[PDB]
Image: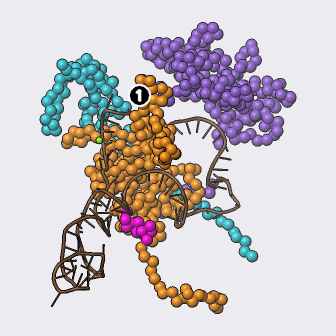
Amino acid sequence: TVGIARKLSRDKAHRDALLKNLACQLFQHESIVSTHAKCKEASRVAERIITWTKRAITTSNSVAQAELKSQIQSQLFLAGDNRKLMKRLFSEIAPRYLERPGGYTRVLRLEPRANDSAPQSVLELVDSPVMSESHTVNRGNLKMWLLVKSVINDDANQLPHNPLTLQNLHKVAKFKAEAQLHGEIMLIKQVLLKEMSLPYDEALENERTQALLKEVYSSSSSYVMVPRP
Amino acid sequence: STRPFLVAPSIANSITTEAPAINHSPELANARKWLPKRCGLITRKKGMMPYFDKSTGERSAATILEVNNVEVIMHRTSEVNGYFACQVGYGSRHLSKVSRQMLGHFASKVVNPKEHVAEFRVKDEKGLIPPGTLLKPSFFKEGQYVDVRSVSKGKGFTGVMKRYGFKGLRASHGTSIMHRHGGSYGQNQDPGRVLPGRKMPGHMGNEHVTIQNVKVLKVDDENNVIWVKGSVAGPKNSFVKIQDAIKKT
Amino acid sequence: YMVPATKRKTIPVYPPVQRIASSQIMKQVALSEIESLDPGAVKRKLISKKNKDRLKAGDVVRIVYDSSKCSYDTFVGYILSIDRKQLVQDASLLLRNQ
RNA sequence: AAGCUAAGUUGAUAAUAAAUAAAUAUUGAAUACAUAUUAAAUAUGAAGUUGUUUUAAUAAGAUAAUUAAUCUGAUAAUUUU
Ligand SMILES: [Mg+2]
């Protein structure tokens, strides 16, 4: 009771309702902005739900499967725009994480909101598909977009990529096919260029992307450690 | 090759005399003190579990003290430092965590960058151990008694009811809005103030505690642990110090 | 006029003697204790959550004490509960008799 | 379940020693005796004193480092002992 989770200045039931709601919204929209604390707890729930889904998908035991399904049902409000959410979890959301061991959600710190000074954050699903057909882009993963923007900026400036940026890119790649990733980047890039003032040469851009990918993929003091004399 | 120096007659003719023994001298104080003969070792409180005496079949609550990488770094003497003591280190620590100065110090004494350094004060020069030498749990015998030092769990800001076991007030018989309060905190005008050391709410715990005469139950070099009978102060992973006891030597 | 030529010496850093995983110790100790206590996991088998024919609330049981250790009489009781704990050796059971 | 808790567990009630209070003495004049000394010398003597033990503060001293590709700190992030 004391120190197992956040309390969030709400009594039990209400808190539970809030958290379930947040999870549902995250599943719906892929990315949401809220207070930091709320995000932090919401992620815990969401991750657990995802894992349950995964287990249901995998495990042979019928009994286990049923139980997991029940748990999933319990942990959601399947009513309005969440009516088909159960289906979505199994069919669309859970598969993306089949190989990934935990860390399905990403919390990113924003600026504290001006009126209230409450510290804010983005909570979002990790590998969310950025390109929906009959739509162009999707309301996807902010981090990826940010990375792409940074890359573009670097290119514009003709500076080398920051090591941090490279690390981030590598992380993104780890659970991602190369070609797919490249495609995603390309999709992002055009859109970004359109948004910004910058021009767009297709082939050149492609080449740049390829170069970026290559470095990412194929991997490559005053104190002297010495034995006790 | 002389220098221009003078000298007063008052100071030249002053007969030599030795200053007598001051009680507030370090040397004198040393003599007074009731110190252990041997040294001790630094340990980490890991947890608690039950020891079973196999003959009598009796259950003793025992706390496990882990003696990882304990090593004498250097010692202090009456001539230089005014007391006899050995600085013992415990446990390895990563370069990144250690100050350059401290690294240098460690190098000076051919040890690895330690996790916790502590002096153990001893009686006489005999008690000192050669520096750079390792200590094991085998330094203590099962059955012997030790004195343990560690830092108690912090209770944060505590009321007088919890700190000093004040009785508080009655629960329901008129009593209003003061159920756990300390009551009067002084007398009227004829002190006209609150006396120093009045028991009052405030921080409790996270303080040093010496617990005396604890029995060493077991000592296993293969596991790097000592077993002590009873409860030792502080949380899991707190640094503890054990010396051989003075009351039951 | 000699300028002071500073020289920041490269400080050596020696490795530790012993090699202990402090995070494992407790478990190891527990294991050792259990080995000491019940050779061949006999007492452990009953009370095992993986054994089907274990002890359950509802079982009536006769506890037989060793005569060499103590001089206690043997006790018969209906098990109300088996108390399983974080570590193994301190498990117990609570049984009654009218 | 953890945690917190006592009705639970564990431990302590700090020695050894120094000088003493009331008191108890030795020798021994001043005062041919007597007198433990409100004389010179020499002794016993208390849960009291000094001290010890315990905690907090202070920081003499000691070890090391020296304008720095990872010197010592702070700001910042994830946190709980
Ligand atoms: Mg007691």
Instruction: Please name the residue shown 18% across and 19% down the image.
Output: C98
Q: Is residue B30 magenta?
A: yes
Instruction: Please name the residue shown 48% across and 59% down the image.
Output: B111
The crowding category of the residue bearing disc 1, from other C-alpha atoms within 10 Å (few below 14, some 14 to 19, many at least 20), is few
Q: Colour of chain A?
A: purple
Three-letter amino acid code at the position of disc 1? Arg
Q: Quadrant of ligand 1?
A: top left
Instruction: Please name the residue shown 63% across and 91% down the image.
Output: B2
Which residue is nearer to you in this view: A75 or B3? B3
Which residue is nearer to you in this view: D20 or C11? D20
Q: Chain in cyan?
A: C
- In which quarter of the view is residue D16 placed? bottom left
- In which quarter of the view is residue C31 placed? top left
Give, as a single range, the part of the protein colored magenta. B22-33
Q: Colour of chain D?
A: brown
Q: Position of residue D65 (x, y in %)?
A: 61, 62
Q: Position of residue A150 (x, y in %)?
A: 75, 34
Q: Colour of chain B?
A: orange
Callout 1 secondary element? loop
What chain does badge 1 belong to?
B
Vertical arrangement, residue B97 with respect to residue B61, above or below: below
Q: Position of residue C86 (x, y in %)?
A: 37, 31
- Along the horizontal axis of the image, is A159 left or right of B199? right
Instruction: Answer yes or no: disc 1 within 8 Å of ligand 1.
Output: no
Question: According to the image, label 1 marks what residue?
Answer: B170
